[PDB]
Image 1 (cartoon, chains in turn orange, purple):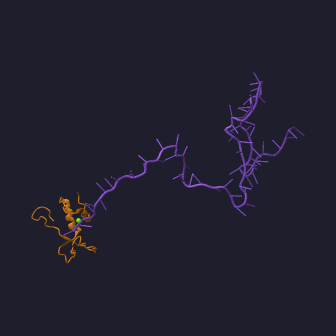
Image 2 (cartoon, helix red, strand yellow):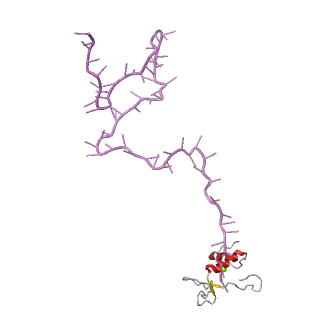
Image 3 (cartoon, rainbow, N blue to C red):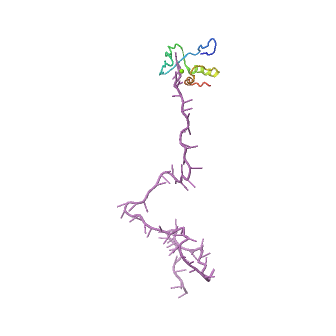
Length: 86
RNA sequence: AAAAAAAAAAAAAAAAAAAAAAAAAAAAAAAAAAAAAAAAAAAAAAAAAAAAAAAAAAAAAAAAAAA
Ligand SMILES: [Mg+2]
């Protein structure tokens, strides 16, 4: 979401669910609260894949000087496998 | 006229040198002189002389998530 003050202050530009191919063990609804929303005909979302689209998006926002506020982001970036600098 | 075979098997043979009382020399200070198997027989590995071994390297984490 756009953390900058403006007309889209806090308005998302990404709310994307995962195009996941194989079987997923845990839904982790106590940790994530997914529907599961990772259905392709039952999207109810922009069910979008990382493969060069949104990984490029976050990578470019890393690249351009757009700092990433939020909570507990360190291990999040680890499980992403992005290495956001200091 | 003491005048002997002139060398197998790589045969085989020389030395390449001394107490010197020559003249009026006492009784081991040597540094130690020191042989036995063979009835189926003697039998260290680790790396081998402590002539001076202080020998607990602090700890504390109230706990996660990730709605
Ligand atoms: Mg958390």
